[PDB]
Amino acid sequence: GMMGELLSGQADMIVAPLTINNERAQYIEFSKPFKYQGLTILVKKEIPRS
Amino acid sequence: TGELFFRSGFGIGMRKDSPWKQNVSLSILKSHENGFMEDLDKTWVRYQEC
Amino acid sequence: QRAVMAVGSLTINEERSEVVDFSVPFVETGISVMVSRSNFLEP
Ligand SMILES: Cc1sc2nc(COc3ccc(F)cc3)cc(=O)n2c1[C@@H]1C[C@H]1CO
Ligand SMILES: *[C@@H]1O[C@H](CO)[C@@H](O)[C@H](O)[C@H]1NC(C)=O
C-alpha cells in the first residue's frame, strides 16, 4: 500500500489521515499531530414505529 | 455509538533521511497556534447537526 | 546541558520547537478559559 510505496521511494511526504502506530514508527518517522481522534463504532440509526 | 477507545492521532510520515522534519513540524505548530486549524475544522468538519 | 532529559508539565510552544527537541506528547492540553457559573414544550 501507501506505506510500501513510501518505503520504495515512490513517495517523499504523506499528507493524509494516518494513525500513528509503533510498527509504522519503527520504519517511518512521523511528525507532531495536528488533530487527535480515536476510533468509534458506526451503526445505522433507525426510527421506531411501534 | 460508544464514548472512546484506543484514542490516537494523525500525522505526516516522512523517510528517516528526509531533512524536512523540523521545518515541517514548526510550520504545523505555527498553523495550529495561529488559528488556522480551527478555521479549517469549522470550514470542513463543523456543519449542520441532525 | 544542566539536564539532558526533562520530564514534566512542559507546555509545547513554537519558540521551544527549534531551540529544543521533544517527542510525541502523551496527554493533550492547551489554552482554555475557566469562568465562574452565574445563576412549556417550547422546542
Ligand atoms: C496521547 C496523545 S495526547 C495528543 N494530543 C494531540 C493534540 O494535538 C497536538 C497538536 C500539536 C502538538 F504539538 C501536540 C498535540 C495530538 C496527539 O496525537 N496526541 C496524542 C497521541 C500520542 C500522540 C501521537 O502524536
Ligand atoms: C529550514 O528552514 C531554514 C530557515 O528557516 C533553512 O535555513 C533551512 O535550509 C531549511 N531546511 C531545509 C532542509 O531546507
Image (cartoon, grey):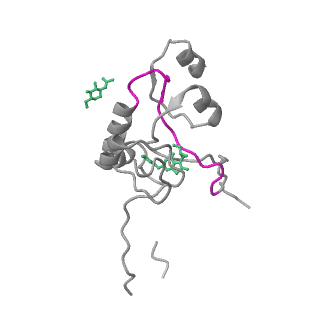
Q: Residue at x 46, y 20 (%)?
A: B17
Q: Residue at x 41, y 30 (%)?
A: B21
Ligand 2 quadrant assignment: top left
User: Which quadrant would residue C17 be assigned to in this image?
Assistant: top left
Q: Position of residue B13 (x, y in %)?
A: 49, 28
Q: Position of residue A23 (x, y in %)?
A: 65, 31
Nearer to the camera, C25 or B2: C25
In the rendered image, the vertical position of residue A2 relative to residue A22, given as above or below: above
Q: Residue at x 56, y 21 (%)?
A: A2
State the extent of the magenta-drawn residues as a range: B3-21
Q: Position of residue B1 (x, y in %)?
A: 65, 54
Q: Quick check: is A5 in the magenta stretch?
A: no
Using residue C8 as the reference point, say whether residue A40 is left or right of it.
right
Q: Position of residue A32 (x, y in %)?
A: 45, 40
User: Which quadrant would residue C29 be assigned to in this image?
Assistant: bottom left
Q: Residue furthest bottom?
A: C39
Using residue B21 as the reference point, say whether residue A9 is left or right of it.
right
Using residue C4 as the reference point, say whether residue B36 is left or right of it.
left
